[PDB]
Amino acid sequence: RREITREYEAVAIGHMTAGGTVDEPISRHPTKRTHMAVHPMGKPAVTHYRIMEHFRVHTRLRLRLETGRTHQIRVHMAHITHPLVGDPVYGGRPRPPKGASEAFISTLRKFDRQALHATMLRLYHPISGIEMEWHAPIPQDMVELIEVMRADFEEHKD
RNA sequence: UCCUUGUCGGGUAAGUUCCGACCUGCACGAAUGGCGUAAUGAUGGCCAGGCUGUCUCCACCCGAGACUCAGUGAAAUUGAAC
Image (tube, protein in one colour):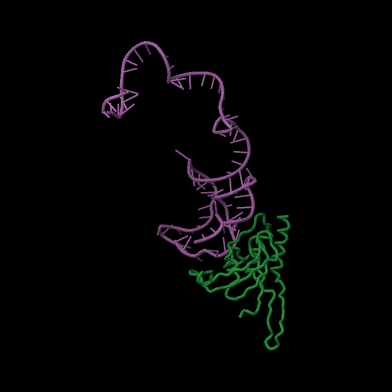
């Protein structure tokens, strides 16, 4: 019935403008067996995305995922040609920004994992019926990732 | 194999060419030889310093033609032409 609400924290590339919804059917990739690409005759899917703040050529954003299928959040974020930061399988080729500092380039090399994190989960108790709310602290790699981007954005553009 | 010439750096105010690198890269490929290689090359491509009419923008001058006169004297083409 799609009752449980799930929230995700992600970092993507590009200067975003506004949030919205994506509704694209998805099936298996015709050629590569480790990719799950968008297909017009695929399984219907719904995903929503919002933005909390922008950066130089990247962004920090909060979004909610309805169906927790295999790598749903990555492709729907990549179907708008705005791939995730550091994603090796679904994210785009590395593209450092103009006038990037050496420390910034190292951070992207250091952050060699996918930019995804779940912070807030809401559930209904089995035998009580009272909502529980929990929050997940931002992981250390993401803390430095947003820190280096904040310093770079406040130095180049400003 | 593709997308945002791939995009960051040098080179430039601005670089579809050049240089070591990120990757989603592995085909070639090890005597139909593979890697590196000092020196060498009227060898391919790029950059820098001096230099200049290459150029903005050409101007003048020196000579040989082009022009007139005297002599000799072709050419390809041509159905006919007011």
